[PDB]
């Protein structure tokens, strides 16, 4: 990787993200006026926690499937050994979904796109996860404040997944090298777009894994 090889990695990560983003950004922004009515919100609140869990678990499964496909398109990831592909997706997929959620979040009214319309955190009252759901919305709010672009999400989430510090890697030197190349690509693309500012404004990695860890615990109770 010299400079044109750095610039090639960027466009490839940004194309792979575009092809697996699940919902187009244009349709998320256009739908910000299609908000759940007061009556539709009550309908969600009256449902059992089990019904809301089956909905959310199946939406989380569909979101994770697109995260796997984004990785399966990453130049480098597909040459790793099967155990390494698995170890990276096991530790990183849920964090990637959390970062990805910021595109579907509207900071103007603290709502998220869910099942066809925008709804506040009150929509998920039946789960009994108000504290966890508040932190999820507050993390998405801190990423939406920065106006996180599609390509920033693409490169940033590629670094969330390609991390050599994951305990269980069989070829930790290969991941470290892919991680190193993605970092040059991310830091270079911030310079090309005059966005160097967002680095110090991004959430600390510990906050992303601590939010993810709490969410993983909720997946049982
Ligand atoms: C129709 C459509 O395309 N949609 C866009 C995607 C959207 C979606 O998947 N959701 C699920 C939705 C969501 C809420 C809550 C959870 C939980 O894990 C649950 F146990 F209930 F399963 C919880 F423990 F946290 F409570 C998972 C997913 C959403 C707000 C969300 C997404 C990602 C991360 C955090 C929250 C939005 C569902 C609607």
Image: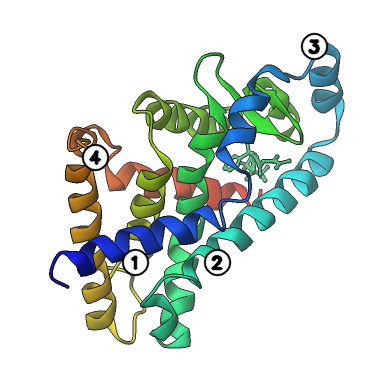
Q: Percent from the top left, x then y, of residue 149? A: 39, 38
Q: Nearer the viewer, mark 4 or mark 2?
A: 4
Q: Residue at x 54, y 46 (%)?
A: 215
Residue nearer the viewer, 58 or 155: 155
Q: Residue at x 56, y 51 (%)?
A: 21
Q: Which residue is mark 4?
A: 193
Which of the labelled discs sits on residue 68, or is there none? 2
> Which of the 4 image quarters holds residue 165?
bottom left
Please say if 74 is above or below 17: below
Inspect this view and state whether residue 129 appears: no
Q: Of callouts 1 and 4, which one flags the residue occurring earlier in the amino acid sequence?
A: 1
Please say if 152 is above or below 178: above
Q: Could you tell me how far apart the alpha carbons at marks 4 and 2 are, in whole angstroms?
A: 28 Å
Q: Percent from the top left, x then y, of residue 173? A: 22, 82
Which of the labelled discs sits on residue 38, or is there none? 3
Please say if 153 is above or below 126: below
């Amino acid at each position: 990787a010299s400079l044109t090889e750095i610039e090639h990695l960027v466009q490839s990560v940004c194309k792979s993200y575009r092809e697996t983003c699940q919902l187009r950004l244009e349709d998320l922004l256009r739908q910000r006026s299609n908000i759940f009515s007061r009556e539709e919100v009550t309908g969600y609140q009256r449902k059992s926690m089990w019904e809301m869990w089956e909905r959310c678990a199946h939406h989380l499964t569909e979101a994770i499937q697109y995260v796997v496909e984004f990785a399966k398109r990453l130049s480098g990831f597909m040459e790793l050994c099967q155990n390494d592909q698995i170890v990276l997706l096991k530790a990183g997929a849920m964090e990637v979904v959390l970062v990805r959620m910021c595109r579907a979040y509207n900071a103007d009214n603290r709502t998220v796109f869910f099942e066809g319309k925008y709804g506040g955190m009150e929509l998920f009252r039946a789960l009994g996860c108000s504290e966890l759901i508040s932190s999820i919305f507050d993390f998405s709010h801190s990423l939406s404040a920065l106006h996180f672009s599609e390509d920033e999400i693409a490169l940033y989430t590629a670094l969330v997944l390609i991390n050599a510090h994951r305990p269980g890697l069989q070829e930790k030197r290969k991941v470290e090298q892919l991680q190193y190349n993605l970092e040059l690509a991310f830091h270079h693309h911030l310079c090309k777009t005059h966005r160097q500012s967002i680095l110090a404004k991004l959430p600390p990695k510990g906050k992303l894994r601590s939010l993810c860890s709490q969410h993983v615990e909720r997946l049982q109770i």
